[PDB]
Length: 148
Length: 153
Image (cartoon, rainbow over all chains, first blue to last red; front, side, top):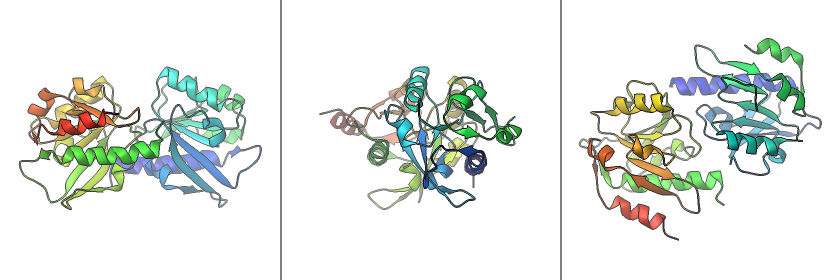
């Protein structure tokens, strides 16, 4: 199987890792993951995931302009969006306990809590401490030991 | 407005439609489709497709800078790429008989044969004669019947 498929599977594994360091105010029986925007590496997420603790992660695509993104998702996995679309998305996320992760992220200072860098021999990611604090979920500090 | 799963399913069928007007100089037993770059609407495609005559369309993602896109695929469905990535992709396709379709309607100026516009009530598309002429495949002009009817309320 190809490198894109290889990297897609690793993206799955990395996200499950990140998830285990996150807590929701009220924990759902099924973790809702929404994939939003064009993505290269979200095909493994979209097949479904299950946490170590047994909880099912349900994932589906949703539109960038879906006004209910914040209430529909516990996790958002954010693909390519222009500036106005990005702003649009996070206005919907505001005030809801949503873990946000972007597939690309050279800057990772505006928007998502975490930004993957899928290129190179291994996946790495950056953390946005500000986003992390305004996000609504509790991020265990150990996860920062897993960032680049 | 149309949902993502609805647009994805419809993209499948417009693509099958477009495929029906195309001829490869040596028709393969199995049509190979490669999805290249970030896409919103390719999840239907990537389940694999079947053509009206029963030829299977196998689909898979591949890296933007894979130098063998031209030989690996009969069809390419192109997602979001920057100016250099696009350049890389269409240089890989030159001299090979490849049908290219973009998810977004801006790429018909830069190498793509067809350009989907997935917004609105229907999926519509536009096309580029230069890119078609150099493609190495034959494209029947009635494929625009599909475009016009799609653009009609």
